[PDB]
Length: 224
Ligand SMILES: Nc1ncnc2c1ncn2[C@@H]1O[C@H](COP(=O)(O)OP(N)(=O)O)[C@@H](O)[C@H]1O
Figure 1 (cartoon, protein in one colour):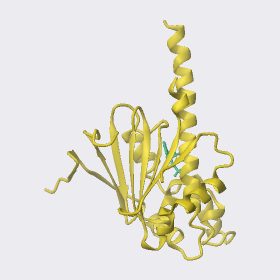
Figure 2: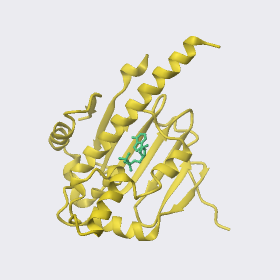
Figure 3: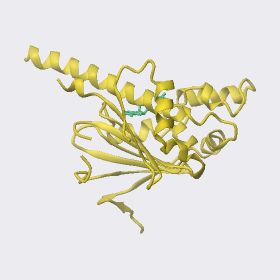
């Protein structure tokens, strides 16, 4: 009897596997973690997303030619906003459609996270060592109360949001013409934990970009 809308579209809420959510909570909120790695992980995903776009564009062209460009614009952008307490990482890479977004981001036990958890379980790894593994996107929760993802694959924009407390939400944004992701891309908005405002600082971002960028072959732009 209660249908939910956000920005003009119905909101679909999905539950995480409860047990997994429980343990994920422990590792991202654990004391003595290397919280900095969240940026390593997101930049790594942004680079992969640009690589995927480049490769698919090249193949498309081959097939368009045979019958029957902006690869140069590929970039990763990082924007702190001290007043809103947000850090935003944006790529103009492949993006995700609704389905990929629910199935890809909607499952916590990824490859690296599952690995880590199993080692902990087998007594082979300490539970504060999230950094020692490549857990990917969900590492954003090392430093965030809430995470949003706005991603466009082809003419449609979808928003994913979660505070990692049992569920995530997905809804379409029909008129995202309020913000100029051009062709495709993914915009990740981190709503930072109170104790994590140093990630709003220019010198800190630069330091991390330098530590985690050495092998990333797409330009990274830090605003301010
Ligand atoms: N920035 C991004 N752009 C496009 N797709 C993205 C993305 N960040 C994550 N994704 C998709 O979500 C999936 C899950 O991400 P993650 O949990 O970091 O797993 P991973 N590091 O093993 O790839 C990725 O494999 C990728 O397909």
